Amino acid sequence: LTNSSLMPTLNPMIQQLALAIAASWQSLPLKPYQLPEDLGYVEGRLEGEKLVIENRCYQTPQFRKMHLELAKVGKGLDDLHCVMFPEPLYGLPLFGCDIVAGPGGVSAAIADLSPTQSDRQLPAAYQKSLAELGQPEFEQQRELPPWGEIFSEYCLFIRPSNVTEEERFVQRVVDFLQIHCHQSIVAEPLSEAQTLEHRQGQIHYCQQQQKNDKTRRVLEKAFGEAWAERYMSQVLFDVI
Ligand SMILES: C=CC1=C(C)/C(=C/c2[nH]c(/C=C3N=C(/C=C4\NC(=O)C(C)=C4C=C)C(C)=C\3CCC(=O)O)c(CCC(=O)O)c2C)NC1=O
Image (cartoon, rainbow, N blue to C red):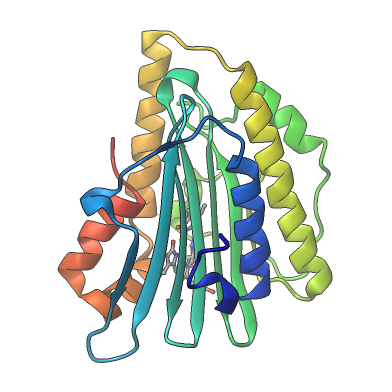
């Protein structure tokens, strides 16, 4: 991230999360993942503010696509988006996070390990490890929208109320990533029927994420409807 144009000007929580995700990935058996049109940096404006986006994307044998996106709209909204899309053959859950900030601080902090099984449960090893972290206390919880039925019972969706909560959130994401990277070493390839189940779950996850009109409006204000539809369906939440 030392080469990032956006990092130096992003919200401090976002900065720490970007670093933590990058650190988690740094020693993995990474290969490039080429986004559509080999996208890296992109910017656009229409009648209002400009949107700037920096994309990084990788893959490993366990993760089909590892995408970390940083964005800023003018000087007033920052975002971090990250999804680790699993390879269905290994049946791992989906790691995701979305952090939205403005000049008055973080407005939304979301992180999850989301199920891909038909029964909408995380694998047993994840349930146990997540349970062992304890129920975190956050003063300003937010209710997920209906499309957010895709998220697990361990999903965080808050407005951080103070620095202690920002740090607690980051630490919880660090803990999710630690659990996830360990489970990815002990996963073994699944049966064809199980693989198919997990593929289904990942498709559903992407279709539901595409219902997020708050993201879509940010993109549309800078690039227009057609661009935004392509971005959400081909770059952010591609249906496999
Ligand atoms: C260019 C990329 C990008 C942008 C611009 C973006 C913006 C964005 N996401 C938001 C919400 C949100 N974002 C999520 C969740 C997620 N979203 C994800 O991309 C992932 C991976 C998850 C979860 C793992 C949810 C649940 C909300 C709240 C939606 C709502 O309030 O209706 C919001 C509203 C913030 C608020 O209400 O305080 C904005 C502006 N998200 C992005 O990804």
